[PDB]
Image (cartoon, rainbow, N blue to C red; front, side, top):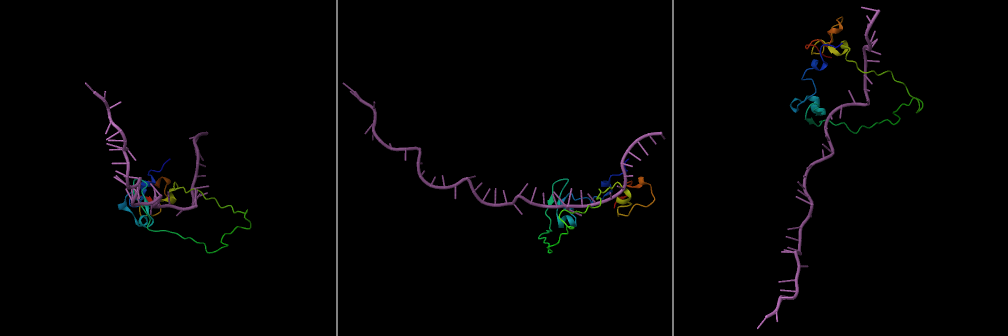
Length: 113
RNA sequence: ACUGAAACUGUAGUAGAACCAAUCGGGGUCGUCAAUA
């Protein structure tokens, strides 16, 4: 079954991605913006460039170019685990412990973590 | 009731000036799944 409320309704309109040039937040101004739900874009005021590795033997190959380490499983994030991803208010407090699972994503006055 | 003749619609003139194919984005990461009896 479904939680009562969609996560987009638990995030404030002042925190959603910007949709107007008049509502560009600090990081939208510094790093730039393109409107995903309309017209509008801004070139970033910050540019990263000239990334130079200073060390030459910087890459560990673990003995041979044909060796590899198998990494631990990197699973998909599962926001449906409300106790981890839902907040008990808009200021980002965790859900209270002990409550029924139905109590995540339940109230408009709840929030995202 | 005696055809005029002969005469290059040519000569000069740059389809061009201006305009960034561009703006935003870490190749990233964890909780189950399934519905009967």
